[PDB]
Structures are given as structure tokens and as C-alpha cells.
Image (cartoon, rainbow, N blue to C red; front, side, top):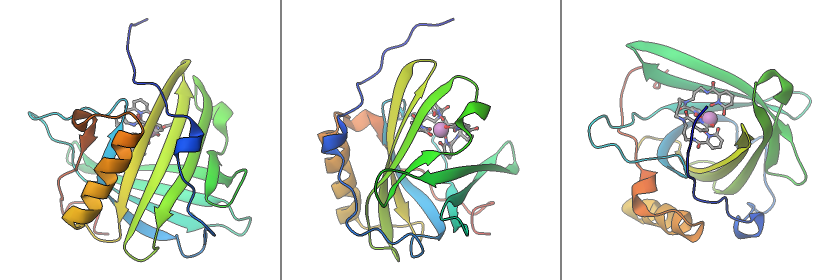
Length: 177
Ligand SMILES: O=C(NCCCN(CCCCN(CCCNC(=O)c1cccc(=O)n1O)C(=O)c1cccc(=O)n1O)C(=O)c1cccc(=O)n1O)c1cccc(=O)n1O
Ligand SMILES: [Cm+3]
């Protein structure tokens, strides 16, 4: 029981796919250095904290994906499964039925060099509402102004204005494990 208004998801034709995606090289820990999306809102009062997301390639070529967040003074863990989709670097969420309200969930790796940075596009439909976000990943907690400007540029090309783009503040708790 609500109302809400969302910037429309871009057509998928506007979201590049990393050429020749290498699933093994993409494994390991990534820090979320940038976040943009139609439900992302810059909040001056209570700024969003950096978290990390860990990709583990399984025998069957799906990823176990684990995100580690610092919240309420504890380390919080969200584990889920990315199942290979229609082309290399594209995934759907495994076990979608087990998430109530969730009808679709798409992941597309837009670009990466595997050992420093990545951008990843996510689109999900939940309670019939269409959310999308772009994540900027670093292998470390810092990235250059140049890379962050590129991420802002790309986010805008998908219809997002600046106040729907945030750069989570680096922290030491939980995510350096
Ligand atoms: O709009 C999006 N994100 C920005 C707002 C995130 N948020 C605020 C943060 C909440 C805190 N958590 C969520 C951590 C726990 N998660 C979940 O138990 C979960 C279960 C099933 C599906 C799913 O998606 N989740 O998250 C993150 O910081 C976190 C970390 C890592 C990955 C991740 O996804 N999240 O959120 C929301 O409440 C929200 C609003 C609307 C849709 C939505 O999916 N979420 O999570 C979005 C668009 C498309 C796919 C997608 O996954 N997301 O999040
Ligand atoms: Cm989410």
C-alpha cells in the first residue's frame, strides 16, 4: 500500500556488455565505490557507507555473491546466486521464487579490467515496479576522478541526474576482511 514515482529503466540497447567477459578473472572482492540508480538518493544527513561484494565462481559457472555491510554496529552479510544468462557477463538471480514480490532480476557487466575497476548494471522488477542501478566497483576503496567522472557520464546517459548518484564513504569496519 503506497504511491511512488520512478525514472524509467533505460532500454538494454543503451547498456554495453564487456566484450569477451572472463568469469574467473572477475572473482574476488570488489568495493562499491560508486552507486547510481532510480531509487538512489543523495542524503546529506546520513551518508551511505561503502560496502564490499565478493564473487565466487562455482563448479557449475554460477557465482556465489556475498555482500558485506556495516550496519547497526555489526557486519551484515547478504548471500545470493548469479546464474549465467543470455551472453557472457550477463546473469539472472537464482532462486527468484524465494524472494517475495520479485519477478525479474538482470545483471550485466558493462566494463572491467578485472584488477582495478568495474561497472555493473542491475535491473529488477519488484511489486511490479522497475528499479535499476549502476555500481562502480574498485579492487581498492579509491578510484581516480577520471574513472568517477566516466561513471557519472554513463549514469547520465541512462537518464539519471546527479542527485541520483552517490559515492559511498570509505570505512574500515567489516569490509577489509
Ligand atoms: O534500486 C536499487 N538499489 C538501490 C536501493 C537499495 N535499497 C537500499 C539498500 C538496502 C540495503 N542493501 C540491501 C541488502 C540486503 N538485500 C536484500 O535482502 C535483497 C534480497 C533480494 C533482492 C534484493 O535485491 N536485495 O537487496 C544494500 O545496500 C545492498 C547490498 C548489495 C546488493 C544490493 O542489491 N543491495 O540493496 C533498497 O532498499 C532497495 C530499493 C528498491 C529496490 C531494491 O532492490 N533495493 O535493494 C536496485 C536496483 C536493482 C537491483 C538491486 O538489487 N537494487 O538494490
Ligand atoms: Cm537490492
